[PDB]
Image (tube, rainbow, N blue to C red):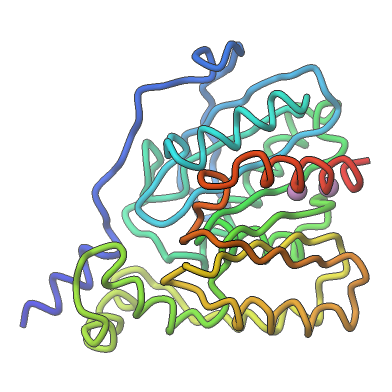
Length: 274
Ligand SMILES: [Hg+2]
Ligand SMILES: [Hg+2]
């Protein structure tokens, strides 16, 4: 019977909020509020770097824009590279509204809302928009690259590909619960959150924009072979999809190999951000 409460808690996770701000990176910023199509109010930072290009970094499940080992470094990196940055918390994370997360489904509305906000309020600073996502954020980045015409390129670090397999592996990673418990709790999580299945490999047919896939060999959530499958399929229609296989755990390439990560992603963004 405790499956019910597990299912609820996994789509209504506790909030994680850090203490640092872009001022600590030496940049002025604005605290902003972004409203989605389905009326969720998101919390974020708008960091004007005087560019006509903006990059949107997207965080993982149970995390937030503050994540010390990947979000703080990627925001610091983007600002050093000279991009404007819009960094928001996904629904039900950090300081954002929304009771439930759907770990990649309705979160496309969060990204679409951020893109609309840029175009509505700062069009001159968002003539080009790139996305960089980690984990759940990497899935949303892939979906956004396909569905949102205003996004010109994307980086997907450790993207879930087989979502139920990754979901099951996630029981241990996020909650220290057994993998076998996933099939019992998932129907409750679905019921509470309204989250619907996503055919990720379908996006291998629709993405024709530059896409940089990163996957680590020690990732316990996503197999190299799963991301390799996405890559090989997409390369049939996309000459500019790339795959970088690293020796790191889940979303920790930027932590373990910071110089390598920033070098490869920096050059990718320079090539495709206009
Ligand atoms: Hg781009
Ligand atoms: Hg990008």
